[PDB]
Length: 266
Length: 6
Ligand SMILES: [Cl-]
Ligand code: NA
Image (tube, rainbow over all chains, first blue to last red; front, side):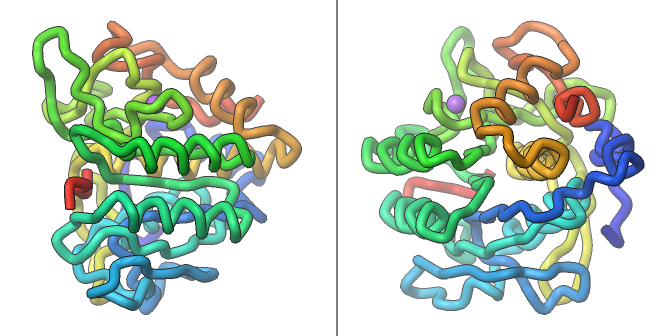
Protein backbone atom coordinates (compact mmCIF):
# COMPACT_ATOMS: atom_id res chain seq x y z
CA UNK A 1 0.00 0.00 0.00
CA UNK A 2 1.24 3.56 -0.77
CA UNK A 3 -0.23 5.08 2.48
CA UNK A 4 1.64 3.79 5.58
CA UNK A 5 -0.64 2.44 8.34
CA UNK A 6 0.28 1.07 11.78
CA UNK A 7 -2.59 -1.45 11.46
CA UNK A 8 -0.77 -3.97 9.23
CA UNK A 9 2.12 -4.46 11.73
CA UNK A 10 -0.35 -4.42 14.64
CA UNK A 11 -2.09 -7.66 13.41
CA UNK A 12 1.37 -9.25 12.66
CA UNK A 13 0.70 -9.41 8.86
CA UNK A 14 4.45 -8.55 8.07
CA UNK A 15 5.50 -11.90 9.67
CA UNK A 16 3.31 -13.75 7.09
CA UNK A 17 4.50 -11.51 4.20
CA UNK A 18 8.11 -12.45 5.27
CA UNK A 19 7.14 -16.18 5.19
CA UNK A 20 5.95 -15.50 1.55
CA UNK A 21 2.14 -15.34 2.18
CA UNK A 22 0.21 -12.42 0.63
CA UNK A 23 -3.29 -13.92 0.06
CA UNK A 24 -2.64 -15.26 -3.49
CA UNK A 25 -5.69 -16.85 -5.21
CA UNK A 26 -8.25 -15.54 -2.71
CA UNK A 27 -11.43 -13.78 -3.90
CA UNK A 28 -12.60 -10.99 -1.51
CA UNK A 29 -15.94 -9.26 -2.16
CA UNK A 30 -16.17 -5.71 -0.78
CA UNK A 31 -19.93 -5.10 -0.25
CA UNK A 32 -19.84 -1.33 0.10
CA UNK A 33 -20.09 1.97 -1.84
CA UNK A 34 -17.97 0.67 -4.78
CA UNK A 35 -14.20 0.63 -5.37
CA UNK A 36 -12.65 3.50 -7.39
CA UNK A 37 -10.88 1.02 -9.82
CA UNK A 38 -9.13 4.00 -11.46
CA UNK A 39 -6.89 4.18 -8.29
CA UNK A 40 -3.36 3.33 -9.59
CA UNK A 41 -2.90 1.20 -6.39
CA UNK A 42 -6.04 -1.06 -6.69
CA UNK A 43 -6.70 -3.91 -9.15
CA UNK A 44 -10.35 -4.90 -9.07
CA UNK A 45 -11.06 -8.29 -10.70
CA UNK A 46 -14.83 -7.83 -11.18
CA UNK A 47 -18.02 -6.62 -9.54
CA UNK A 48 -21.63 -5.54 -9.70
CA UNK A 49 -23.83 -2.66 -8.55
CA UNK A 50 -27.21 -3.34 -6.88
CA UNK A 51 -27.87 0.40 -6.12
CA UNK A 52 -30.32 1.42 -8.89
CA UNK A 53 -29.42 5.16 -8.67
CA UNK A 54 -25.64 4.40 -8.80
CA UNK A 55 -25.03 1.85 -11.57
CA UNK A 56 -21.18 1.69 -11.61
CA UNK A 57 -19.47 -0.47 -8.95
CA UNK A 58 -16.02 0.68 -10.21
CA UNK A 59 -16.66 4.25 -8.99
CA UNK A 60 -17.09 5.29 -5.37
CA UNK A 61 -18.95 8.54 -4.60
CA UNK A 62 -18.78 7.91 -0.79
CA UNK A 63 -15.05 6.91 -0.19
CA UNK A 64 -15.57 3.98 2.27
CA UNK A 65 -15.45 1.12 -0.24
CA UNK A 66 -12.19 2.37 -1.83
CA UNK A 67 -10.57 2.84 1.62
CA UNK A 68 -11.63 -0.66 2.77
CA UNK A 69 -10.41 -2.21 -0.54
CA UNK A 70 -6.99 -0.60 0.16
CA UNK A 71 -6.89 -2.03 3.72
CA UNK A 72 -7.64 -5.56 2.43
CA UNK A 73 -4.71 -5.24 0.00
CA UNK A 74 -2.42 -3.61 2.63
CA UNK A 75 -2.97 -6.84 4.69
CA UNK A 76 -3.18 -9.27 1.67
CA UNK A 77 -1.39 -7.64 -1.26
CA UNK A 78 -2.22 -10.57 -3.66
CA UNK A 79 -5.97 -10.85 -2.84
CA UNK A 80 -8.42 -10.48 -5.79
CA UNK A 81 -10.91 -7.69 -5.01
CA UNK A 82 -14.53 -7.57 -6.19
CA UNK A 83 -16.51 -4.31 -6.01
CA UNK A 84 -20.09 -5.10 -4.95
CA UNK A 85 -22.01 -1.84 -4.61
CA UNK A 86 -24.77 -2.26 -2.00
CA UNK A 87 -24.52 1.25 -0.42
CA UNK A 88 -24.97 4.61 -2.13
CA UNK A 89 -22.89 7.79 -2.02
CA UNK A 90 -24.37 8.66 1.43
CA UNK A 91 -23.10 5.29 2.74
CA UNK A 92 -26.71 4.01 3.10
CA UNK A 93 -28.42 0.95 1.67
CA UNK A 94 -31.54 -1.28 1.68
CA UNK A 95 -31.64 -4.88 2.92
CA UNK A 96 -32.55 -6.12 -0.58
CA UNK A 97 -29.40 -4.57 -2.21
CA UNK A 98 -27.26 -6.24 0.47
CA UNK A 99 -28.96 -9.61 -0.16
CA UNK A 100 -28.41 -9.23 -3.92
CA UNK A 101 -24.68 -8.54 -3.21
CA UNK A 102 -24.41 -11.64 -0.94
CA UNK A 103 -26.15 -13.79 -3.60
CA UNK A 104 -23.77 -12.42 -6.32
CA UNK A 105 -20.81 -13.31 -4.04
CA UNK A 106 -22.11 -16.93 -3.69
CA UNK A 107 -22.82 -17.22 -7.45
CA UNK A 108 -19.28 -15.90 -8.22
CA UNK A 109 -17.45 -18.25 -5.77
CA UNK A 110 -16.10 -15.54 -3.44
CA UNK A 111 -13.84 -16.86 -0.60
CA UNK A 112 -14.46 -13.89 1.74
CA UNK A 113 -17.20 -11.24 2.07
CA UNK A 114 -16.52 -7.94 3.88
CA UNK A 115 -19.58 -5.91 5.04
CA UNK A 116 -18.38 -2.64 6.68
CA UNK A 117 -22.05 -1.70 7.31
CA UNK A 118 -24.78 -2.15 9.86
CA UNK A 119 -28.37 -1.55 10.85
CA UNK A 120 -29.61 -1.39 14.46
CA UNK A 121 -32.53 -3.81 13.77
CA UNK A 122 -31.42 -6.10 10.96
CA UNK A 123 -33.41 -8.21 8.48
CA UNK A 124 -34.62 -11.85 8.59
CA UNK A 125 -33.99 -11.95 4.78
CA UNK A 126 -30.38 -10.71 5.26
CA UNK A 127 -29.94 -13.34 8.01
CA UNK A 128 -31.04 -16.11 5.59
CA UNK A 129 -28.62 -14.78 2.91
CA UNK A 130 -25.52 -14.56 5.21
CA UNK A 131 -26.33 -17.95 6.75
CA UNK A 132 -26.56 -19.42 3.18
CA UNK A 133 -23.20 -17.78 2.32
CA UNK A 134 -21.54 -19.31 5.42
CA UNK A 135 -23.14 -22.73 4.71
CA UNK A 136 -21.68 -22.52 1.12
CA UNK A 137 -18.19 -21.98 2.64
CA UNK A 138 -17.72 -18.15 2.47
CA UNK A 139 -15.83 -16.39 5.29
CA UNK A 140 -18.26 -13.57 6.15
CA UNK A 141 -16.77 -10.61 8.09
CA UNK A 142 -18.61 -7.50 9.21
CA UNK A 143 -17.98 -4.30 11.13
CA UNK A 144 -19.37 -4.75 14.69
CA UNK A 145 -20.92 -1.24 14.52
CA UNK A 146 -20.06 2.29 15.68
CA UNK A 147 -22.82 2.53 18.36
CA UNK A 148 -20.51 2.73 21.38
CA UNK A 149 -22.00 1.33 24.57
CA UNK A 150 -25.51 1.07 26.08
CA UNK A 151 -24.98 -0.16 29.67
CA UNK A 152 -25.39 -3.96 29.71
CA UNK A 153 -27.12 -3.98 26.25
CA UNK A 154 -25.40 -5.29 23.11
CA UNK A 155 -24.82 -2.50 20.56
CA UNK A 156 -23.45 -4.81 17.83
CA UNK A 157 -25.18 -3.94 14.53
CA UNK A 158 -26.73 -6.32 12.00
CA UNK A 159 -25.50 -8.32 10.20
CA UNK A 160 -22.42 -8.55 12.55
CA UNK A 161 -24.77 -9.57 15.39
CA UNK A 162 -25.69 -12.89 13.67
CA UNK A 163 -23.73 -15.94 14.91
CA UNK A 164 -22.71 -16.94 11.33
CA UNK A 165 -20.90 -13.58 10.78
CA UNK A 166 -17.54 -12.56 12.30
CA UNK A 167 -18.22 -9.34 14.25
CA UNK A 168 -15.08 -7.09 14.26
CA UNK A 169 -14.61 -4.27 16.75
CA UNK A 170 -12.08 -1.46 16.54
CA UNK A 171 -8.98 -0.75 18.67
CA UNK A 172 -6.64 2.21 18.30
CA UNK A 173 -2.81 1.93 17.91
CA UNK A 174 -2.59 1.39 21.73
CA UNK A 175 -4.93 -1.68 21.62
CA UNK A 176 -7.63 0.29 23.51
CA UNK A 177 -11.23 -0.16 22.37
CA UNK A 178 -12.19 2.89 20.25
CA UNK A 179 -14.99 4.84 22.05
CA UNK A 180 -17.33 4.28 19.03
CA UNK A 181 -16.70 0.48 18.77
CA UNK A 182 -19.92 -1.55 19.43
CA UNK A 183 -19.95 -4.02 22.35
CA UNK A 184 -21.81 -7.16 23.37
CA UNK A 185 -21.37 -10.91 23.64
CA UNK A 186 -21.66 -11.09 19.77
CA UNK A 187 -18.33 -9.22 19.41
CA UNK A 188 -15.78 -11.81 18.10
CA UNK A 189 -12.40 -10.10 17.50
CA UNK A 190 -10.81 -6.65 17.32
CA UNK A 191 -8.64 -5.06 14.69
CA UNK A 192 -7.12 -1.60 14.10
CA UNK A 193 -9.83 0.93 13.24
CA UNK A 194 -8.67 4.41 14.37
CA UNK A 195 -7.13 6.89 11.85
CA UNK A 196 -6.27 4.13 9.31
CA UNK A 197 -4.61 5.63 6.21
CA UNK A 198 -5.80 4.01 2.95
CA UNK A 199 -6.88 4.72 -0.64
CA UNK A 200 -9.61 7.32 -1.34
CA UNK A 201 -11.46 8.13 -4.59
CA UNK A 202 -9.90 10.48 -7.17
CA UNK A 203 -6.43 8.91 -6.65
CA UNK A 204 -6.25 10.29 -3.07
CA UNK A 205 -5.29 8.80 0.32
CA UNK A 206 -6.32 9.59 3.87
CA UNK A 207 -7.24 8.44 7.35
CA UNK A 208 -10.69 7.17 8.33
CA UNK A 209 -11.97 5.71 11.61
CA UNK A 210 -14.61 3.08 12.27
CA UNK A 211 -15.34 -0.63 12.75
CA UNK A 212 -15.56 -0.24 8.91
CA UNK A 213 -11.71 0.04 8.92
CA UNK A 214 -11.30 -2.84 11.44
CA UNK A 215 -13.37 -5.37 9.38
CA UNK A 216 -11.07 -5.36 6.25
CA UNK A 217 -8.00 -6.09 8.46
CA UNK A 218 -9.84 -9.36 9.35
CA UNK A 219 -11.05 -9.97 5.71
CA UNK A 220 -7.36 -9.51 4.64
CA UNK A 221 -6.18 -11.78 7.49
CA UNK A 222 -8.62 -14.48 6.25
CA UNK A 223 -7.02 -14.14 2.77
CA UNK A 224 -3.50 -14.53 4.27
CA UNK A 225 -4.64 -17.63 6.22
CA UNK A 226 -6.27 -19.21 3.14
CA UNK A 227 -3.06 -18.58 1.13
CA UNK A 228 -1.08 -20.63 3.78
CA UNK A 229 -3.99 -23.18 4.24
CA UNK A 230 -6.04 -23.17 0.97
CA UNK A 231 -7.79 -26.41 2.09
CA UNK A 232 -9.14 -24.84 5.34
CA UNK A 233 -12.87 -24.35 5.59
CA UNK A 234 -14.41 -21.05 6.59
CA UNK A 235 -15.08 -22.72 10.03
CA UNK A 236 -11.34 -23.46 10.38
CA UNK A 237 -10.28 -19.94 9.29
CA UNK A 238 -12.75 -18.34 11.75
CA UNK A 239 -11.71 -20.70 14.61
CA UNK A 240 -8.00 -19.91 13.97
CA UNK A 241 -8.61 -16.13 14.18
CA UNK A 242 -10.70 -16.44 17.38
CA UNK A 243 -8.53 -19.06 19.13
CA UNK A 244 -5.16 -17.26 18.55
CA UNK A 245 -6.30 -13.65 19.22
CA UNK A 246 -4.35 -11.60 21.79
CA UNK A 247 -6.66 -11.11 24.82
CA UNK A 248 -7.22 -7.40 25.54
CA UNK A 249 -9.78 -7.51 28.38
CA UNK A 250 -13.41 -8.32 29.02
CA UNK A 251 -14.95 -10.09 26.00
CA UNK A 252 -18.05 -7.80 26.20
CA UNK A 253 -15.72 -4.91 25.06
CA UNK A 254 -12.97 -6.82 23.18
CA UNK A 255 -14.33 -10.27 22.18
CA UNK A 256 -11.40 -12.73 21.98
CA UNK A 257 -9.10 -9.72 21.51
CA UNK A 258 -6.78 -8.44 18.74
CA UNK A 259 -6.34 -10.75 15.72
CA UNK A 260 -2.80 -12.20 15.37
CA UNK A 261 -2.59 -13.45 11.76
CA UNK A 262 0.93 -14.88 12.30
CA UNK A 263 -0.46 -17.10 15.14
CA UNK A 264 -3.76 -17.80 13.26
CA UNK A 265 -1.93 -19.02 10.12
CA UNK A 266 -0.21 -21.89 12.05
CA UNK B 1 -32.26 2.71 3.88
CA UNK B 2 -31.55 1.48 7.46
CA UNK B 3 -28.05 0.13 6.68
CA UNK B 4 -25.18 2.63 7.13
CA UNK B 5 -21.43 2.55 6.51
CA UNK B 6 -19.49 1.77 9.73
CL1 LIG C 1 -29.19 -7.77 8.80
NA1 NA D 1 -21.67 -12.45 14.66
